Length: 46
Image (cartoon, rainbow, N blue to C red):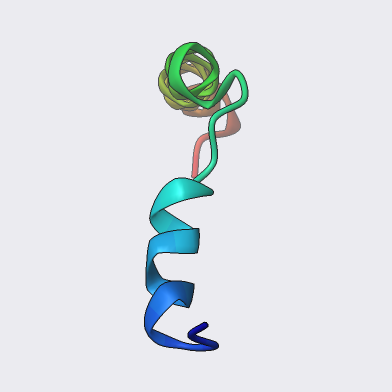
């Protein structure tokens, strides 16, 4: 019958399992591709 010591286990128990493991790699690849776009910026002459 605890209303706070047990809460800390709840977060661990409920950390977050739902496509977060495989899904995290998919978003990471999108960020590297945006970096290549800067090369076209040379045409801007800035």
